[PDB]
Figure 1: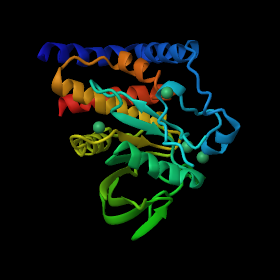
Figure 2 (figure 1 turned 30 degrees about the vertical axis):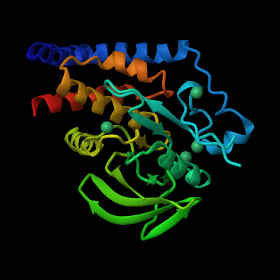
Figure 3 (figure 1 turned 90 degrees about the vertical axis):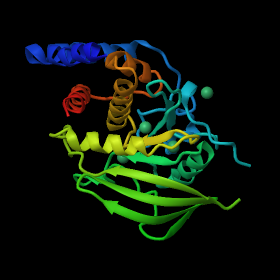
Figure 4 (figure 1 turned 90 degrees about the horizontal axis):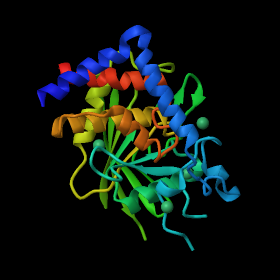
Length: 278
Ligand SMILES: [Cl-]
Ligand SMILES: [Cl-]
Ligand SMILES: [Cl-]
Ligand SMILES: [Cl-]
């Protein structure tokens, strides 16, 4: 209803009050929940899989990890299923792929029936490598049994959309929504561009398709921020009634560190407030 929307908007101001005391309290709770819960990630730590992780301390929880079909530890990718508002396994949250995991990455896309990739990092930021370029600059590239062809590109102010066709050589359209303006440090000054990106990339999800693949560099901070904004917008649209903190605690059981920073937690609320007022 209008009334629960009114209470949420008021709750946002509450969190902001007293030098953001409520936001800090909320996020400290989130971090403590993560610290206290024991969630295994044995596969991520297996010696054979160590080179498949971009970061030694960003793992894939066992219970929610995406499994690749075994090949004649070939089942491992640093990726997890993550819920959306009502829908189980609405997303696959994953790291920016490495050259050594490009074949695995595209095979996962294929096997999962994924039609949309959401990328929320530049390849290099402030001279530091954040992600390897897992797609062809032009024409086609073969990544094991998957051939990926770049059909077309549209470069907007804050995001780029690349339309691919992929084919398993042992054809499907896959669209990449690539946000290109996230700052080197902190969060975006203005939420509106991110809101537009979330709305357009989320609207691209078609019926009877697999999870939307979301990644940044580690696949935790910006990735989690996207998933929470998208999911809470969908909840507001359908139900009203938002529960950002409970949703975040829940997804944090599915992939380590989703929404990594308090600044991101606050940004989520800025973005939802802008959506509500717009
Ligand atoms: Cl499992
Ligand atoms: Cl991986
Ligand atoms: Cl890296
Ligand atoms: Cl979505």
